[PDB]
Image 1 (cartoon, rainbow, N blue to C red):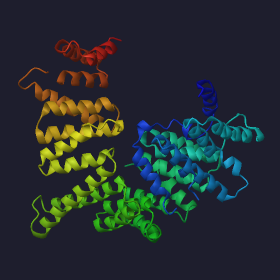
Image 2: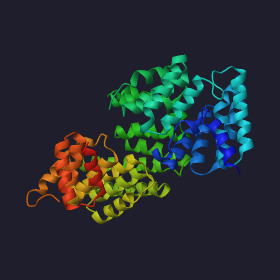
Image 3: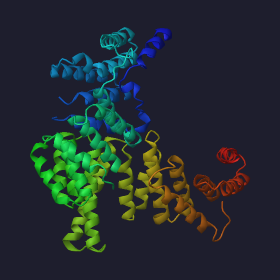
Image 4: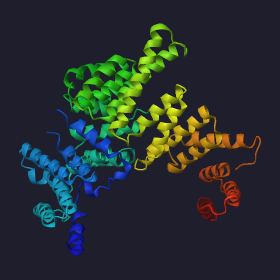
Length: 471
């Protein structure tokens, strides 16, 4: 089992264009969620190729290399299915993935078989490169993979899709990928509306793209036109949980609770293991409940009272279900905890938040939001200013640049100031030092951090902060 040969092979592997070389980092996603999403997208539809390649990479990430190979087998079969003259060239990503998986299974001759096929094809076609072949289809596959890896990848996805569109501006698939990417980037904004209309025009039969157009129309207060698209696709998506859950989102945002629930129930029947779906159901119940409490001025009577009680229990049931199906699905923890807190059940909220705070292997984005919500809980329900500060600070440390940034910095100032009502600053000095360092006030930051070091001369955090401010 030679490290020499392993690294020699690896040098070739790094030359390939495929999921293993596209810097798709497991740290940036919830693997189980991404796996669930891809499985749903594959349901009851051919266009399955990119999804199978990607799913194989995801299986590898989960430590299921055999399942990975199963996915590549399916990808290969689909390529065969197209029966096109472009088989060899259409096979490069799948082959690259095969090479990497076999490499990770300590099976080097097999891996080399695939690198061989790849190099051979690149040779035949006189590629400027030995193991890659410039290809719009590949740019498209890459775009899809990046998109699936989430917000840290959207710009990259957009670039990939643009690159493909460079070659074929009116390719139906490339336009779907581009339009979806711009939609995700809109998440509010409406830059995606034109691209979405064009994508629908190029894909008249496609429910997936229509549902997103409908959502963007809803966003810009064109609810009737949107709803027309939803009705156009309803009969066709009955076994497609991925499309169903977005159509259900459309209804939820229109306050059509029962319709939303109807589609989500259909979706769950196709994929009952899905945390995402259970969580969507929870959001629906919760939203209706909030609506009734609002209309009833927080004093629902009679049947309204019965309904709110039922809705609270259903929401709780589904948030719990989501958590049971994926302990990493952080949103279900925060939504559940927040429901408890709103009902005055502080001990229950605390239990759930505590669980969430102890989850190490979740994404920084989720951690950022968990700290934010626990901070708010501390501030408005526990009335613990000190603890709120701690957690707003942790949220900022995890993610300096997010939508919550201003709220966090502001709140930190406020609370630190409340501290000075009766006591010199203690936690609070660190908070102000951090915030002014962040906002660019080096002098102030320095002062605060100096006081902090005074109090805790051993604190490596303050030491590092002061090392940096020293510059």
